[PDB]
Amino acid sequence: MTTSQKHRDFVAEPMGEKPVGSLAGIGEVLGKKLEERGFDKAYVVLGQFLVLKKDEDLFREWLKDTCGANAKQSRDCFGCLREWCDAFL
Amino acid sequence: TTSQKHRDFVAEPMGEKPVGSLAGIGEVLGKKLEERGFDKAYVVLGQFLVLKKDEDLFREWLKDTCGANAKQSRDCFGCLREWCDAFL
Image (cartoon, rainbow over all chains, first blue to last red; front, side):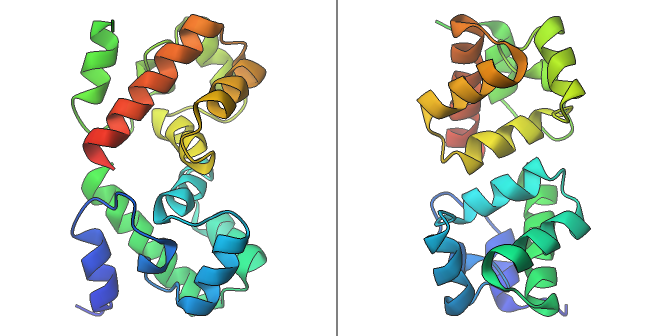
C-alpha cells in the first residue's frame, strides 16, 4: 500500500460528521480555507465530488480554485473520496 | 408515513441507482433532473450534502430545478435524510 495511513483511516469507515481535515491531502492550511468557504465537514466536500459526477478533472480544479490545493493534495483528496464512495455509497 | 419506494431506497447503498429511485421523483421530475445533469441519485445526494442537509434550501432547490411540488420535495428530502443517517 502506497496510500497514507490518513487515507486508509478515512476510507475504512463511514465519515459521519468528520471535519474536512480528516480527508487525505487536506492539511490544516487547506482545511481552514475550505471551512472559510463553507466546506466545514468532510461530507460537504463529498457533496461537491458527487455533484461533479466524480470527475477527477473538475473536482481537482474545484479544489485548486477553492483552497489553493496543489497537484498532490488534490490527487490525494480525490482518491480518498473515490475509494470512500467505492466502499460505502 | 412513507412509501415502499422510500423504504427500498433507505435500506441499502444507492450506488449507481438512477435519479428515479428517489422517493418523490417520478417520471416527469426524473426527466427534468436528467436534463439538468442530475441523472443518478447520488448527484442529488451531492446537492443535499453541499447544502449541508438544510431542508428548506434543498426542497427549494428541487422545486427550482425540476418543478417538484411540496409532497414530492418532502418525499425526496426525507429519503435522502434517512439514507444519510444509515450510511454516511
